Image (cartoon, rainbow, N blue to C red; front, side, top):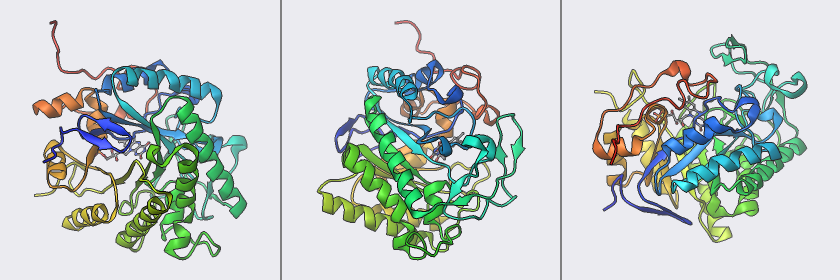
Length: 377
Ligand SMILES: Cc1cc2nc3c(=O)[nH]c(=O)nc-3n(C[C@H](O)[C@H](O)[C@H](O)COP(=O)(O)O)c2cc1C
C-alpha cells in the first residue's frame, strides 16, 4: 500500500516519494529575471525523484501583481530559468513551472503604462483586502477592466506561448494557476463573474476560459506535461462561489471529458483547501471541507495533489487512506530546505518567518534557512 514516502508514476514521470514543493511567490526574481538566488532556492529543496512546483510565473506584462516575480514570456527570462531547471535536474528533481495571471488582483504600478488590471468584471476587490506595493507599503486594489472575448483569446495565447517557453527552458511541465481569486478564478467564481456573454452565467460558461487554457497548453506541449490548480472552497480576495462542491465537480467533469476525448491524462489535478485552526495548519480539536476534498478526488480520473495546512501526520494519512496521491507543502518548505528528509525522520521543523516571505534579499529569509547537519562522511 502507498505511503507518503512511496514511489509514484505521475504519468510520464517517476517520483520516489509523494512530498511536493507547493508553488509559492517569494519575490526574489529581481526585474522578473530568474537568478542565482532562485537557482540555490530550488536546488536546496530538490531531492532525487522529488516533485517541485515553482512560484507563480508571469505569462505577460499584465500578469503582474507582486514585485520581482519571475516571468517566462521573454528570452532573457527563459535563459534565467534554464539555470534553475538544470540545477534541479542535476539533483534528480522533477520540476513544473506555475503559469500565473493575477487578473484584477493587481495595481496600476504593476501594469504596463499604468493601465487598469484586467478581469472578467469591472468590480474591484473590496477594501477589506490590500495589495503589497513595490515600495513596501500596502495599497488599494483598483477597478479592473472587463476583457472582451477577443482579448480573452489573447490571454489564452499568452498561456500557450508561456508553456512552449517553459519547455524550452527545460521544465518537465507546467501548472495552470486557476486558484486563489486570480484571473481564471475571477471567471470561475459566481461571486465575481457577472458577465452576460458566453463567458458568464452557467458553470459551462464560467469554466470556458480555464478549459480553453488547458486545451491550448495541452496541444502545445502534451497533456502529460500539464497540471491544473484550483481552489473552489477558498474565497481569498472576495473570490467566493455559492456552490463550491458543484464548481469543483464542474471543472473535474470537463477535465475528465477532455482526457477521454484526447486519449490521455493530464499530469494532475491540484486542489488547495482552507483550514480552520489558528495557525492554518492541521485540524481543530471542518469535516465539510474534508468530505469535499475526498469527493473531488473520487470524481477526478487521474493524479490528485492536495495542499493547504497539511502536517506530517495529515500528509501520511492522506496518502495511506487514498485521499490523495501527492501532498504539497508550502510554508514548511520555506523554512525547511530538507523538508523531505525531515518528514522521513520525523525531525523538528524550523519555524518560518512570514516577515521575509515577500522581501527581496537573495539570502536573508530565502536561502539561509538551515538543513539538518549532515556532518562530514
Ligand atoms: C508566501 C506564499 C506564497 C505563495 N505563492 C503561491 C503561488 O505563487 N501560487 C500558488 O498557487 N500558491 C501560492 N501559495 C499558496 C501555497 O502554495 C499553499 O497552498 C499554502 O501556503 C497552503 O499550504 P501550506 O499550509 O503547506 O503552507 C503561497 C503561499 C505563501 C505562504
